[PDB]
Amino acid sequence: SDALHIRFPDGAVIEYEPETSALTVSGIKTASVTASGSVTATVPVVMVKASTRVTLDTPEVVCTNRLITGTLEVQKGGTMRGNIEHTGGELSSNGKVLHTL
Amino acid sequence: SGSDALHIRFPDGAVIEYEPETSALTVSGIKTASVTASGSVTATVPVVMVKASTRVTLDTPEVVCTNRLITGTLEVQKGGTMRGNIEHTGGELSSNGKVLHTL
Amino acid sequence: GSGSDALHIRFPDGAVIEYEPETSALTVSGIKTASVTASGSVTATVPVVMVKASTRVTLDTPEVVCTNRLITGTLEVQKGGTMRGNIEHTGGELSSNGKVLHTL
């Protein structure tokens, strides 16, 4: 009643290891969680290793501080407030480079 | 492999189940879920799909996208930096009340 | 009842994994790490998702897609990109290669 180690016929496992306080779900194909209110995770580090794609299908994604990306595609429009510093290439608008490199 | 089974049917109508033939884990019929951890939470899977009819909030010092980020619209509140070539088309890029391609 | 109709596990490290049907709340607490490894996909369908990560959220993926609006405090684009439609900048200076493009 105080332990968790489930081993399914397809090789999937759900286990909790109290020595390292580690919860593991492995060997599954899909997971789906459907809730009517909220899903919350509170932890210093979140790591999502997704070899195809992460889709956030929502009216609004909010990042409360910094957002860092390799490349950016804004599809429809946007607003920017504050100081914005572009360097290391050329910023073009409507086919016109705004400050040649 | 093992022979364990998971199919919990709770009195509020929620279900937690694993189906090994299709290797599908399902959690249904709940109101809330939370995970609170002192170290890390990791998900390793090709596709992550979040369908959130109100909002997704990432309340963190830093969200890092290692490659491409695509959005419908963007709002930057407190500034930033852009490196590389940035190609703007299909509308007006305005700064401080002037359209920049016609300045 | 006597069947599989409940979930409440308290582990010797103080962690809890439980489902509380009175409030329909699934809770994992008191752990150090969690991981989920799947070969196909993970889906979460719920009105509100909240991730409170006091160090970082890393999305290590070819593509992150936000289907509608994305709001951020600050933005850092490292390699380049594209923008379509109207992009309205105010409340500071937009500089390119060391030149302020329009002073208010």
Image (cartoon, coloured by chain):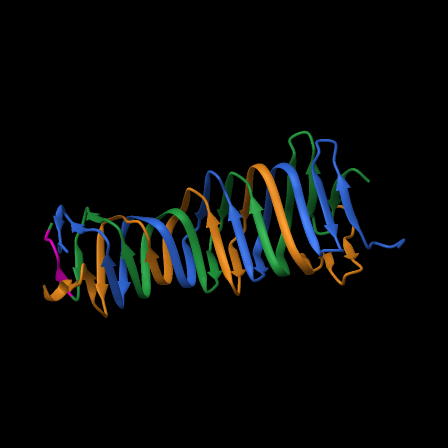
Chain colours: A green, B orange, C blue
Percent coordinates x, y for residue A90 in the rendering: 16, 53
Residue A1, quarter of the rendered image: top right
The residue positioned farthest toward the right in the image shown: C2
What residue is shown at x 70% (from left), y 52% (from top)? A10
Q: Does the magenta stretch include residue C88?
A: no
Return the residue nearer the eye: A17 or C95: C95
Return the residue nearer the eye: C10 or B83: C10
* Total number of numbered discs in the rendering: 0
The answer to whether residue B22 is seen in the rendering is: no
Residue A77, quarter of the rendered image: bottom left
Percent coordinates x, y for residue C75 in the rendering: 32, 49
What residue is shown at x 15% (from left), y 56% (from top)? C104
Percent coordinates x, y for residue A44 in the rendering: 51, 38
Apparent side of residue C89 relative to residue C56 in the rendered image (left or right)? left
Apparent side of residue A40 relative to residue B16 in the rendered image (left or right)? left
The N terminus of chain C lies in quadrant? bottom right
Magenta: main secondary structure = loop
Return the residue nearer the eye: C91 or C88: C91
Tell me if residue A26 comes above or below residue C84 in the rendering: above
- The part of the chain drawn in magenta is A95-100
Percent coordinates x, y for residue C56 in the rendering: 45, 41
Apparent side of residue A64 relative to residue B29 in the rendered image (left or right)? left
The answer to whether residue C43 is seen in the rendering is: yes
